[PDB]
Structures are given as C-alpha cells and as structure tokens.
Amino acid sequence: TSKVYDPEQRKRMITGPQWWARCKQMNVLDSFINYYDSEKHAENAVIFLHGNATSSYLWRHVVPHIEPVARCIIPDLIGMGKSGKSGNGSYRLLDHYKYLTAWFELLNLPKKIIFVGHDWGAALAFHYAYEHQDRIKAIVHMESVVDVIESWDEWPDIEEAIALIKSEEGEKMVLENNFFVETVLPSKIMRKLEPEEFAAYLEPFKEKGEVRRPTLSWPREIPLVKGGKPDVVQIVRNYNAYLRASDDLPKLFIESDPGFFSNAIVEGAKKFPNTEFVKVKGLHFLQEDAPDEMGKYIKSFVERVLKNE
Ligand SMILES: O=c1n(Cc2ccc(O)cc2)nc2c(Cc3ccccc3)nc(-c3ccc(O)cc3)cn12
C-alpha cells in the first residue's frame, strides 16, 4: 500500500526554505533559537510548541488562522529545526525547558499566555504552567504527555516498545536510520507529503549520527513509572495533579484517531476540568491532515477565552 498526494495541497505548499526565510533568530544562553513571530496583536501571545521529529514548520498552515486575533510565536526547540544546538549536547525535557524559558524572557510577553502544545511540546507547556501558574491564560493540547503511565495502566507491550527505544538497537534505529523522520513521521500522516515538505522535516537530521540525538532523547523521557526517568515522572506527576485541579484554566483538547500510544492520552485529558473537546480525522501528526479544521477550532476557542475574560 502507499499513500497519495493531496492534489489541492501543492498549490499552497510552503517549502522549508520559504518558511525559514520567514523566521528570526535570537541568541539564548550558550546557543540560539529560530522562531516565527507574527508580531501583531501583541496584547495576547499564542505560543505553539511542536514535539518530537518536527519543528515550527509543523504549524505553518495552522498559524494563519490565529494571527488575526493574537501574536503567534512558534519556536524550533533546541537542537531541532533551524535552532542552535544545546551547549552540553543534552536534549532531555529539562534541557529543552532551560532554553525555552530563557527564550520566553526575551520575547516581551504579556502576563497571561496561551499555549498550543503537541506531543512533548505539550509537556513543556504543562511544566511551564505548573511552575508559573499565574502566567497561563489557556492551554490547547493534542497528542500530549498528559500523565504518567502507572504499572496498572500499562497496555500490552508498552514495556517492549520503551525497552526497544532505550536499547542500543533503538539508538541505531534513530542515529543511523533516522527512524522518527523517515518512518514514524510519514506513517502517522494520512496523505503523502509533497517531496519539499518531507525535505523540510528531513533537513535538520539529514546527516547520520549524533545530530539526530533530540529525536532519540524525547521518547526516552517517557513517564513510564516502570523504569522511566525519575525526574520526568515527578515532573509529570506534579503538573498532572495541577491540571486535574485547575477548574479556572480554560483548555481545548484536539483528539485524533486512536493509536498504540493514543488511548492513554485521551483518557488522561478528560480528567482535566474546563476542557472543550473537538475531533479531527488524522493520526499523530494531525496538523498535516487537518490544519485548517485545527486552526478554525483553535481560533474559536481563543476568541471565546478572550471575550469571556
Ligand atoms: O507505534 C509505534 N510507533 C509510532 C509512534 C511513535 C511515536 C509517537 O508519539 C506515536 C507513534 N513507534 C513505535 C515503536 C518505536 C518507539 C517509538 C517511540 C517510543 C518508543 C518506541 N515501538 C512500538 C512497539 C515496539 C514493540 C512492541 O512490542 C510494541 C510496540 C510501536 N511504535
């Protein structure tokens, strides 16, 4: 079987170099962050955070829907997209968080921020929110790291999968074969990407070896209490308890099709109060199959949050 191009998508395609020319760079700590900033309507800030395998490019067709109502800021996480590399070559959640929060300090942000998070980008938003509970206006999340995986909540073979990614076989899958870009990314998009769109995702990780480390380090942070990184399990424990009790924080959850990793996410998200639920037909990288539906859903949600404020 093979997937097929969307015949109407090529008309509006934005290549990597087209996107990267639209971005800015700012030095941050011992490195720098590449990011997109629509600048206008700076009274609010909507910060879009990608997760593993991707970059700010993931949001290119989503963000135009929100720009008319709020300043949109979209970083490439450290070591990803066109950003700088981490000073110590470490790419754990806390390394990403260190660069992200230092970048926030330089952005002239409003007091209360709106976050839109996918995958580990949602973990970063949730952790920031837990540590800055007075800085959060609303959180949109999707395919998110919502909670830990307790021993009794393990589903069949999650043990196998995490042992695989933490093994040397997993390291070679990523560092040598570029598993998350070459395999996972296209496998979790329903359409076939245009060659230029795939090239934009490949470009940061085109060379073999250690440059692909961020895409290996992210899954190894998974908060499986059985053998998971204790610091990340505690981080997720803390922000999950905060989210479960955050009755006054408006949230939007965008659901996609069920998957091997997906079922724990949706059940965890329904434990957070004040959550508006919506659905798009897509897989994990749902931005590539329903960007306009997503953008219109986020826009209505932001409009409702602001008007009701
Ligand atoms: O579906 C999937 N993806 C696709 C996917 C990846 C990330 C994401 O966010 C959503 C979807 N990837 C796997 C992997 C490899 C892997 C990836 C990331 C972390 C840990 C392991 N391994 C298994 C598996 C291996 C043995 C086994 O017995 C059962 C399952 C399934 N995978």
Image (cartoon, rainbow, N blue to C red):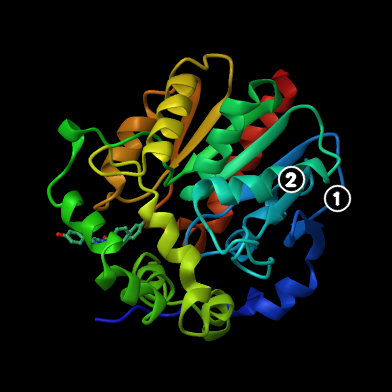
Which residue position is annotated with label 2? 102
Amino acid type, residue under disc 1 in the picture: Glu
Residue 122 vs 30, above or below: the answer is above
Residue 158 vs 208, above or below: the answer is above
**Residue 114 in sight from this viewpoint:** yes
Residue at image coords 30%, 32%: 267
Q: CA distance from mark 2 to mark 1?
A: 19 Å
Q: Is residue 212 left or right of residue 171?
A: right
**Circle 2/circle 1 CB separation < 8 Å:** no
Q: Is residue 165 left or right of residue 66?
A: left
Q: Position of residue 117 (x, y in %)?
A: 55, 45
Residue 4 vs 142, above or below: the answer is below
Amino acid type, residue under disc 2 in the picture: Ala
The quadrant where ligand 1 appears is: bottom left
Residue at image coords 63%, 76%: 13
Residue at image coords 34%, 39%: 265
Q: Is residue 296 left or right of residue 237?
A: right
Q: Position of residue 305 (x, y in %)?
A: 67, 26
Picture quarter containing residue 10?
bottom right
Q: Secondary structure at mark 1?
A: loop
Residue 58 vs 246, above or below: the answer is below
Which residue position is annotated with label 1? 39
Residue at image coords 29%, 60%: 166
Residue nearer the viewer, 117 or 160 = 160
Looking at the image, the residue that sits furthest to the left is 156
Residue nearer the viewer, 103 or 166 = 166
Q: Position of residue 251 (x, y in %)?
A: 54, 29
**Residue 118 in sight from this viewpoint:** no
Q: Quadrant of the N terminus?
A: bottom left
Q: Secondary structure at mark 2?
A: helix
Q: Quadrant of the C terminus?
A: top right
Whichever of callouts 2 and 1 sits on the residue coming sooner in the sequence is 1
